[PDB]
Image (cartoon, rainbow, N blue to C red):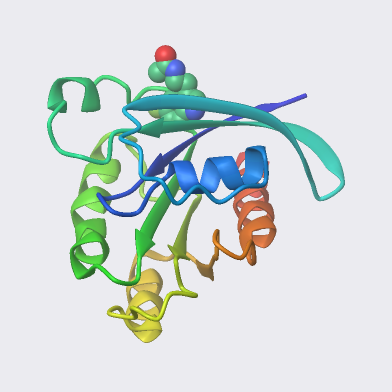
Length: 168
Ligand SMILES: CC(=O)NCCc1c[nH]c2ccc(F)cc12
């Protein structure tokens, strides 16, 4: 069984724990929790083969810069998650891209863009904006709803395939 070390980055107000709990115990936790560092490991069957996904969640708030430049080690797969109600989280993606470009030493890397809380009526970020931005980085934009659990599985399959194809 192969272990995929993936990291989930996001801004304040997104709730990375909402994605983990929804896949772990299939439950949407509305209660916001300041997850500083949480590693969730579960056996997920992708494409028909059972693999282990090691999802590392880190503080989405800016404070521990010392740890931010230290935890970045086993970052095989990157997962950029943002909410369509906050424009800052969407514009912050560029800043992260420039950072990942350095702490990786590679022009190409398996990355995917997922839009959470798309079922929410608070649509402040247009979908075309995400598509246009995604095309610039050269990554696929996948809509994902963790509240009603839709577009979640496909978002994993796609990313896993990207890593698999990249390595092979
Ligand atoms: C740093 C350490 O001791 N453990 C983390 C292990 C890990 C799992 N998934 C990841 C994704 C990115 C990353 F940088 C690390 C991880």
